Image 1 (cartoon, protein in one colour):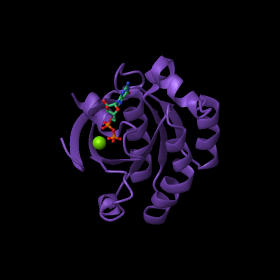
Image 2 (cartoon, helix red, strand yellow; image 1 turned 90 degrees about the vertical axis):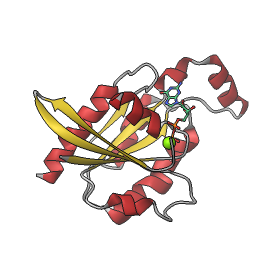
Image 3 (tube, helix red, strand yellow; image 1 turned 180 degrees about the vertical axis):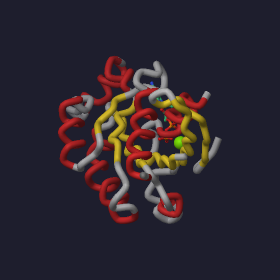
Length: 171
Ligand SMILES: Nc1nc2c(ncn2[C@@H]2O[C@H](COP(=O)(O)OP(=O)(O)O)[C@@H](O)[C@H]2O)c(=O)[nH]1
Ligand SMILES: [Mg+2]
């Protein structure tokens, strides 16, 4: 059984990722049995609040973590910038050994006019997939995987990858 913790800025879609996949509050735990490469594995999902108010409690959730899903929204460059500035340092402070998968969320919004118009008011654009992939390399993430809890694009893949990385580490 594999312990997976999701971290990242508020509003990127952490809670939505886990609920979409496994099917109303700050911190919550989920448990699912998942078929990975043909055999069942128990996956514990710990959903954390990403607001600065925490690190109060948040790192208390980290004990014995096998895999971190470090999430940013692909339509939030600020959340991408926080991967380097806040999240990788925090994870590495508490669990320096644990594998990380860099997870880009809300992929469907790359094609949402309202969202794109809003980003452009500050001359921003969605995070290029190339940039995410390069960062994943820089931070020594296992991989970069981009997904949508709305359309379920790559949602299975995110958690399959989490389990594979998590078993390898655990073992
Ligand atoms: N369009 C779209 N909206 C999403 C997606 N994932 C989450 N949301 C919405 O984004 C907001 C933040 O989601 P939430 O699960 O609360 O994020 P968290 O704060 O990181 O846990 C909510 O309005 C969700 O409905 C997605 O993949 N696509
Ligand atoms: Mg949430």
